Image (tube, coloured by chain):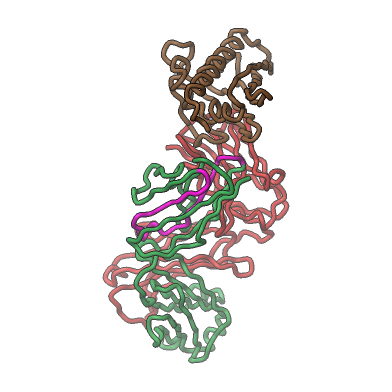
Amino acid sequence: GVFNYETETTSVIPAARLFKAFILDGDNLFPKVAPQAISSVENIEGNGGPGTIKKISFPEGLPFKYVKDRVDEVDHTNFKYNYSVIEGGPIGDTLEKISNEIKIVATPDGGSILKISNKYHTKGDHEVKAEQVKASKEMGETLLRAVESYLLAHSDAYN
Amino acid sequence: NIVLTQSPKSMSVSVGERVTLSCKASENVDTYVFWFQQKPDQSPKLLLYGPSNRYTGVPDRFTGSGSTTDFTLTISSVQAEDLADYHCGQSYSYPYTFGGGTKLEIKRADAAPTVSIFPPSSEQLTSGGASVVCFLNNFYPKDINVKWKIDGSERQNGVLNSWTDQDSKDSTYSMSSTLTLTKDEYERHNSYTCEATHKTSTSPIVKSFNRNEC
Amino acid sequence: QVQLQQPGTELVRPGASVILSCKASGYTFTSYWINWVKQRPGQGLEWVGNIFPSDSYTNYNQKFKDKATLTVDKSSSTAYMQVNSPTSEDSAVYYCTRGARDTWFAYWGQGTLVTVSVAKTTPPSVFPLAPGSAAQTNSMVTLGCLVKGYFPEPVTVTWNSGSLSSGVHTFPAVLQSDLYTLSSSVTVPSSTWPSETVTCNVAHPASSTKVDKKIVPRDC
C-alpha cells in the first residue's frame, strides 16, 4: 500500500532561516532543544549531505529506541527536503518504509508555512494504524515548536 | 553540479618539507568535503574524511581545513611514501564531484642509473623472436636518454621504452628500453650495446655484450 | 572484514553489454549505499551514481544518465553497474564503494578494468632474463624476466611468490599492435644468487594463465 497524509502549519520565522535551522542543522539542534523526544542523532554512513543515513536515538521510555532515516534530496534554494524512514520504529511487518517531504514557504507577512507529506509504503495492503499518523504529527509538532522558541530567544542565530 | 578546483597541477618538495594542497569549489559546500590519497597502482584511499579530519590510519603529518569554498590538505613533513596523487570530493549537492587531483612529487639528490643489458633468452629464440632489454635503474632526474648500437652503428627501429614512477623508498626512477627484432637479423650481428646518457656525467654509462663471445 | 569484491578485468566488443558485479560481505548489504566511481588511465575520478539496496533507490550523474544502469540482487547481496553500447571512451576502471560513519568512500572495491576492443584475448609468453655468460661480477646482481605479447591488460608479476618485494621494478606495459608486453627486474646480493633460487611468478587472470620462470644462470 502507499497512503499519503499531507499536513500544514505556520511559523513566525522566515522560511529561509527556519529552513537552515529546523532542517539543515536541525539534526543536532533537536537533542538540544527537545531532549525528551530526541536523545541523539548520528551519521551511520555519509557526511550529512544528500544520501546521508542517520540513526536517531530516543530517550529511554518512549515507544521506540531508535530509527534510521535517509536524506534523499535537498533543494537549497526552494527549501524542499525529502527523506525516508527505513529501519526501526514504525518500520516492520505492516510498514516497509515512510517517504517524507517537507517544503517551507515564505508567507507575505514574513512568517512561513511547512507542508508535509507522508507516503507510508505498507506491506501489500495492510492499513496505516491511525496510531502512527497521530504521533508523526505530534512528534514533528513539538519539534517545530521547540525550535521556534529557541530561534526566537536567540535572535542572532542561524543568520 | 559543483566544480572542485585543485592547484597546482603538481608539487615538488623534498622529503621532510612541508606542503599544502588547495581545493576551491564553485559554491559553498559547507563541510561536505573530503580528501583521497591515491598512490601509483592503487585504488584511492580515504585520507581526510570531512575537512581537517584524519580517517582511520592516516598519520598526524596529515591535516586540513576550510569550509564555505576554500579548503586545504597539508603535510607537515612529507615522506617518501606520501608520494601520491591527492584528490578532492564534495557531497554537498548531487552529483558528487571531484577535484582534478594534484600530484605530489619528491625531490632528492641526483643519482646515476644502474645499467644492465640482457641478450635474448634461448627460449624466445626457439620461436624466431629476439629481444634485447636493458634496465637503467634508480636514477634522478627523470630525464635520461638511451641509444642502441648494433656493432657501433645506431639503431632506432624496434626499440621500446617505459619508466616507472618515482618509487617510495628512495624517490628514484627507472626505465627500460628493449630492442626487439628477427632471430635472423639478431644473428646477422655481433656486439650489442646499450647507451645511457644521463645528466650526472658528460661521459655516458655503457653496457654491452658480444653475441659471438657467448 | 567488510569487503567489496569485483573482477579485475572485463573485455568487451564495442557495442556489447558490459556487466560490472560487486559483491559485498562483512556488513548488512541493505543498510548501506554503493557509490560507483569510474576512472580512466591517469585521469581524475568521476562519480557515476549511487544506489541504496533494499529499496533500490538511485541517483545518476548526468553524464551517464542513459549509458549506465545500477541495480542490485539483495539475495546474493551484490550490486551491478551495467554499461550499454561501450566504446573506447568507456574503457576504464570502475570502483564500487561504500562509506561509513561520517563519510563516503571509506571502502573501495578492487576496481575492474574494462577494455572495449575487437582484439582477441591472448596469454603472455614469459622469457627469463639472466646475466650473460659474457658477464662480470658486481657487488649486487640483477635479474628479471619479460612478459611478451598478451592481451588484454593487466598482468601481475611477483618474485619468489612475493617474498622478494624490495629491489623489484616492474615496468608499465606497452601496446604493440594489439598485444601488450612488459618487463620486470630484480636485484640481490651476488651471494644469494644463484646459490639460492629466484623465480618470477607472472599471472594473467584474463587468460586464466599463471607462469613461473626460474631464473637460472645462462650457460654455454
Of residue C110 and residue B28, the one placed in the foreground of this image is B28
Compared to B48, does A45 lie above or below? above
Q: Report whether B60 appears left or right of C112.
A: left
Give x and y (percent) for residue C146.
48, 69
The color chain A is rendered in = brown
State whether residue C220 appears in this view.
Answer: no
Give x and y (percent) for residue B18.
36, 58
The color chain B is rendered in = green
Give x and y (percent) for residue C14.
71, 55
Residue B77 part of the magenta segment: yes
Q: Which residues are magenta?
A: B68-94
- What residue appears at the point 67 percent right and 41 percent down from the top-left corner? C69
- What residue appears at the point 55 percent right and 19 percent down from the top-left corner? A144
The color chain C is rendered in = red
Report the label total: 0
- What residue appears at the point 55 percent right and 59 percent down from the top-left corner? C42
- What residue appears at the point 50 percent right and 48 percent down from the top-left corner? C110
Compared to C173, does B158 lie above or below? below
Q: Quadrant of the C terminus of chain C?
A: bottom left
